[PDB]
């Protein structure tokens, strides 16, 4: 638990202190949050016959039954994303950041817009084959970079960004997801827990910048948890890559595209127990390695 | 009119939600399914007369072990699912699922349903199983476990190709017409 | 607007009006443009629309405004009813009306405040009177609420506990907040999400009003009106509002409030039958102080 | 197999939600009712064959005029409701509701459903109406209005006492099955 004796030129200690504070308040901010609990209660009751609901309502344990599964899932996710490295992983992250290419001059807003657009294009064959879609996403990226320039990030900025990154949807679509979704075999936060921890991630991004915490490590953690939270109905991948690439490009690092195909399913905790899931620190290491791999190309 | 409540159980990621969506919508869900399929009612025709078929998905994950049985009351037939390319999910049929539904619904028929047939011929799936010195579950292997665990029969389907998917629920309706008996919440008081 | 710069004010009503002007001016951003609020309207509206019609309508840009127009018009109607913006005549009348209220110099202790709020609830309902066990349970919730809120800023969590404490006959597993828009004798209430949003605004309003020294009897009147109009919780909104308001009153030395007259209560909220004249925010305050002056 | 979609329209506060709850639960709601009753499906056996009856509530308030007709597609029968002790809601049947469903669903049958029968003889209700020089709507007056607006028939019910409530949905099913 103690890192007082380890070399630190990335403010990882200050980063770990932010995660410890957020983690210490996770139970109250999420597990004891009544909007979260009410969501779990309603969803759970939809599968229970009304005769059984009337019967169970006389047992004091009934509320814990309705909410236990939801709380365990969020706790599982929070355990996967909370950054608390070992002494070995701490020094390893120190060496890995030194291997990243970092440009002295930071690109202007127009240039950042193009590079973040191209980073999304490399991930999707549809963006490449569809010039109209790429131009639409380019505008959303430009709008997000204009509104967030020299200003603290806000959830409204992310809502607008996510909506901008979904131009092929059709009118009237819900912004946020309306139910718990599963990706392949992975678990995501409940809609309400995702909204709660989306705002905490925003606070996490601002504090890390104010505290001078290594942006590449910040980008890694932000990528993992946004994907794990999955707040929005669609476009969570695009949105995460745009936010992370802003954090990186603001620091002069190359834009991020995607993890290896073998490593992506390890980011989230899974429903198939045989799949080994990666810890938050392991995600950071593989992120920095992937970022340094783009300095070779 | 008689209604038929069919509850789908089994390990996580065996394809319970997908086989329900592919059966109710005739389209395999592309990209991201709900954790639990929204319980759905369809009017199926059997014997020339209509029956309301109630399809209920469950969360197989361990985190929902206390909540899941509260959906079992007034169930007419269970679909104990396992992936034919997931030996652990097959093992959990004997180790977890059949004991669970038998505890809560002793005299309720259930079918052993092998899911994801298409992956049994997938070379990448065969390769991944071989890494762990594992192999897919043959129909003969699952049919023996169905008789051992007193299952009505073993049926097989692929939600992706819909192969045998319509047949799985046809057998589920036929098993449901074998008269069952009510269910129990076990009543496990705490503290 | 209307000018108050020349009017006599010993209640900090000017500061109260300025608080309401800021909240009202941000109502559109805080509620109507809030995506959690719009998403709720979108999902509820689509539940009644056939899937074939949704696919057709998703090609029309106006579709999203159709899904949320009705919900936005209801909240605007509610906010218009609760926003405190009195005329110069109502301003001066409220000033005189507060001077007529009985105010005890010595403020009661915690145990005494608990009992008086308990009796104030007892007079409103015949059920609590005939059932001593129910009355004893509500007395504990009020005591717990007064202990956790003494000398500390009010929080939504304190209210959530209070509301839950005032619902002891419900049974386990019940949702705390309401799950849908409800209507009571043709009245309109805030949507579940908009009621949560504006419940928090009312909490910030209560704390800010106490710091700014705004007349508590006027604060309690406004708080009573909007809590009832918002109706955030599935049950117990009436009991909960009376407890919070009576705390605001008893903290200032005023008698506890019970209920308006039977003729005036349905005028608090906007109605579904348009022929029913609804009372303005200032008219609710005026009637509130008049009922308080009688006690 | 065959489903019957019945949509309940009419002015706000005429009892649409209550008559749906009272018909589906056989218990008049005493608590605060929902704005719009959650759409409900029952398989009714009245007659010789079973039919799935879909009951759909609407928001009669003017604020929902744009959204409300999006629920009308695939409707088999409408229940244009007015309170027999609310002359304005009766007048809005001719002025708004029948023109609305006729515009969106021209060849869809509808019933004129007078609600809240129990109040027709309530002295306090009659006295309140008489102050405004109004009087409750008699069945003869509504029957005439139903024939003028080409309604299938005029029926009336009280969600509170369930008098004629079961008949209102019986006739709606008959109107949908035999246009
Ligand atoms: N190839 C194939 N994949 C399937 C089939 N059914 C489900 N899947 C996949 O299995 C994964 C988990 O399925 P899901 O419906 O969530 O299973 P559940 O957790 O038991 O509900 C998803 O990635 C699906 O794409 C199938 O019949 N064939
Ligand atoms: N006496 C009486 N009151 C009724 C009847 N139906 C509804 N109400 C009352 O009329 C008010 C409005 O009912 P509601 O269902 O919300 O009307 P809606 O807005 O059209 O859905 C409520 O206070 C009900 O209690 C009835 O048959 N008799």
Image (cartoon, coloured by chain):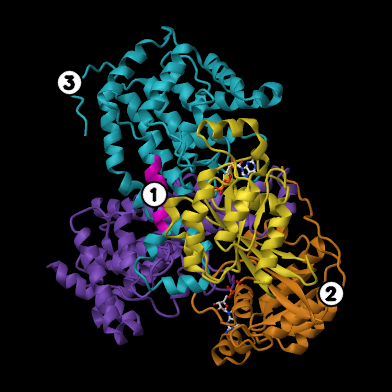
Chain colours: A purple, B orange, C cyan, D yellow
SS at badge 3 = loop
Of the two numbered discs 2 and 3 in the rendering, the one whose residue sits closer to the viewer: 3
Looking at the image, residue B32 lies above or below residue C249: below
**Alpha carbon separation for disc pair 3 and 1:** 35 Å
Q: What segment is highlighted magenta in the picture?
A: C68-78
Q: Which residue is mark 2?
A: B177
In depth, the one of C248 and C158 nearer the eye is: C248
SS at badge 1 = helix
- The answer to whether the residue labelled 2 contacts the one labelled 3, judged by CB atoms less than 8 Å apart, is no
SS at badge 2 = loop
In depth, the one of C104 and B183 nearer the eye is: C104
The local crowd at label 1, few if under 14, some if 14 to 19, many if 20 or more residues have their Cα within 10 Å, is some
Q: Position of residue A242 (x, y in %)?
A: 29, 68
Which label is found at residue C73? 1
Q: Which residue is mark 3?
A: C6
Looking at the image, residue B82 lies above or below residue A211: below
- The answer to whether the residue labelled 1 contacts the one labelled 2, judged by CB atoms less than 8 Å apart, is no
Which label is found at residue B144? none
Q: Which chain is indicated by disc 3?
A: C
């Amino acid at each position: 638990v103690n890192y007082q004796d380890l070399e630190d030129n990335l403010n990882l200690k200050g980063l770990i202190s932010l995660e410890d504070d957020r983690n210490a308040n996770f139970e109250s901010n999420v597990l004891k949050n009544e909007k979260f609990l009410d969501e779990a209660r309603e969803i759970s009751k939809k599968s229970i016959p009304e005769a059984t609901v009337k019967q169970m309502s006389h047992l004091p344990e009934f509320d814990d039954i309705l909410t236990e599964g939801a709380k365990k899932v969020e706790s599982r996710i929070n355990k996967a994303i909370t950054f608390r490295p070992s002494v070995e992983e701490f020094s390893e992250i120190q060496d890995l950041v030194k291997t990243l290419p970092k440009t002295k001059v930071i690109e202007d807003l127009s240039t950042k817009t193009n590079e973040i657009t191209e980073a999304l294009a490399a991930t999707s064959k549809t963006i490449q084959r569809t010039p109209e879609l790429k131009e639409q996403l380019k505008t959303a990226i430009e709008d997000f970079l204009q509104n967030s320039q020299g200003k603290p990030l806000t959830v409204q900025m992310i809502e607008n960004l996510n909506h901008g990154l979904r131009p092929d949807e059709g009118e009237g679509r819900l912004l946020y997801k309306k139910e718990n979704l599963t990706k392949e075999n992975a678990v995501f936060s409940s809609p309400e827990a995702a909204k709660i921890q989306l705002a905490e991630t925003v606070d996490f991004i601002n504090r890390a910048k104010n505290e001078g915490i290594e942006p590449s490590v910040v980008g890694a953690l932000v990528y993992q948890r946004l994907i794990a939270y999955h707040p929005f109905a669609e476009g969570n991948g695009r949105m995460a890559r745009v936010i992370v690439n802003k954090i990186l490009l603001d620091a002069g690092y190359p834009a991020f595209t995607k993890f290896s195909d073998e490593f992506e399913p390890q980011i989230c905790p899974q429903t198939k127990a045989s799949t080994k899931s990666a810890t938050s620190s392991e995600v950071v290491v593989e992120f920095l390695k992937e970022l340094a791999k783009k300095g070779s190309k | 009119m008689q209604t038929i409540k069919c509850v789908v159980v089994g390990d996580g990621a065996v394809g319970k939600t997908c086989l329900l969506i592919s059966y109710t919508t005739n389209k395999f869900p592309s990209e991201y399914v709900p954790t639990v399929f929204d319980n759905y009612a369809v009017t199926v025709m059997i014997g020339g007369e209509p029956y309301t078929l109630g399809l209920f998905d469950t969360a197989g994950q361990e985190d929902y072990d206390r909540l899941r049985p509260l959906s079992y009351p007034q169930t007419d037939v269970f679909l104990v699912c396992f992936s034919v390319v997931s030996p652990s999910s097959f093992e959990n049929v004997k180790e977890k699922w059949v004991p669970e539904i038998t505890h809560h619904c002793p005299k309720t028929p259930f079918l052993l349903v092998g899911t994801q047939i298409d992956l049994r011929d997938d070379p990448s799936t065969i390769e991944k199983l071989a890494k762990n010195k594992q192999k897919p579950i043959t129909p003969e292997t699952a049919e023996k476990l169905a008789r051992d665990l007193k299952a009505v029969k073993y049926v097989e389907c692929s939600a992706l190709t819909q192969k045998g998917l319509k047949n799985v629920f046809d057998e589920a309706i036929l098993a449901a017409l074998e008269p069952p008996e009510p269910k129990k919440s076990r009543r496990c008081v705490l503290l």
